[PDB]
C-alpha cells in the first residue's frame, strides 16, 4: 500500500506521447498507447503533476 503509482511503460507512454501529440489530446493518446485504467482526466492530471514535479 503506502502510495500507489503507475508502471514504467504507462508513464513512458504518457510522457513520450503527450510531449509530441499535445497537452490536450488524451483521446489520441489512449488510441495509440495502451494504459491500465486511463481515460482523459487521469492522463491530464498525471501529466500536469509530472510537469510541476
Image: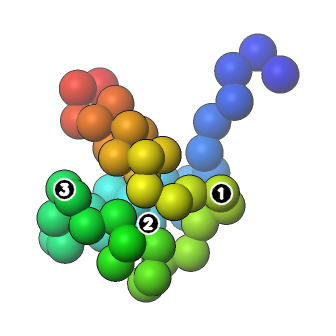
Please give left or right for residue 35 compared with residue 22 in the image. Answer: right
Mark nearer the N terminus (3 vs 1) = 3
Quadrant for the N terminus, please.
Answer: top right
Q: Which residue is drawn at 67% across and 61% down?
A: 36
Quarter of the image where one finds residue 2:
top right
* Separation of marks 3 and 2 at Cα, in angstroms: 13 Å
Image location of residue 15, percent across then percent down: 33, 57
Disc assigned to residue 9: none
How crowded is the residue under tag 1: few (<14 C-alpha within 10 Å), some, or many (20+)? few
* Circle 2 SS class: helix
Q: Is residue 37 visible?
A: yes
Q: Which residue is drawn at 28% across and 36% down?
A: 48
How crowded is the residue under tag 2: few (<14 C-alpha within 10 Å), some, or many (20+)? some
Please give left or right for residue 8 compared with residue 52 in the image. Answer: right
* Circle 3 SS class: loop
Image location of residue 13, percent across then percent down: 43, 66
* Mark 1 vs mark 2: in front: 1
User: Where is mark 1, residue-wise?
Assistant: 37
Image location of residue 21, percent across then percent down: 19, 72
How crowded is the residue under tag 3: few (<14 C-alpha within 10 Å), some, or many (20+)? few
Q: Residue at x 16, y 64 (%)?
A: 22
Quarter of the image where one finds residue 31:
bottom left
User: Where is mark 2, residue-wise?
Assistant: 13
Q: Is residue 12 visible?
A: no
* Circle 1 SS class: loop
Q: Nearer the viewer, residue 52 or 31?
A: 31
Q: How is the model colour-coded?
A: rainbow
Relative height, residue 47 to residue 51 (above, below): below
Mark nearer the N terminus (1 vs 2) = 2
User: Where is mark 3, residue-wise?
Assistant: 23
Q: Which residue lies furthest to the right in this view?
A: 1
Amino acid at each position: 500500500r503506502k502510495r500507489q503509482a503507475w508502471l514504467w511503460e504507462e508513464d513512458k507512454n504518457l510522457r513520450s506521447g503527450v510531449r509530441k501529440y499535445g497537452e490536450g489530446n488524451w483521446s489520441k493518446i489512449l488510441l495509440h498507447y495502451k494504459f491500465n485504467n486511463r481515460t482523459s482526466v487521469m492522463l491530464k492530471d498525471r501529466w500536469r503533476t509530472m510537469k510541476k514535479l
